[PDB]
Length: 57
Length: 57
DNA sequence: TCGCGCG
DNA sequence: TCGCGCG
Image 1 (cartoon, each protein chain N blue to C red):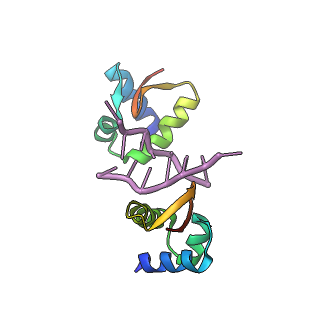
Image 2 (tube, rainbow over the protein chains, first blue to last red):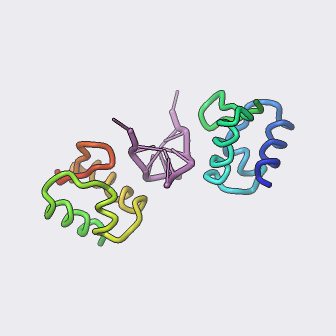
């Protein structure tokens, strides 16, 4: 599950994480990450305080 | 040459052509068309009078 | 009314 | 300072 891996990465970091940093950590392409990230965001489960930058909540 | 085919399609039509209509006519994906279209546009060789709509000049 | 071409 | 997720 990509979703759990993304959440773990973000939670462990604790701060704003760049999409590029998630690629290294999750080992999947940016497009694939963004499909999940934007979904999570619409679910109020992550936020994007900056463009292509992600954090928990 | 995709470039010549795009130009032919646009010239024959004579008016504003939707990206979707170019796919049918050129038989290549939208992304591939747009890479060429935007290049042609930067070359002042096509115009986009509307979003995802293209014409000659 | 989503425009997306992007390196 | 390009944001891109897009169906």
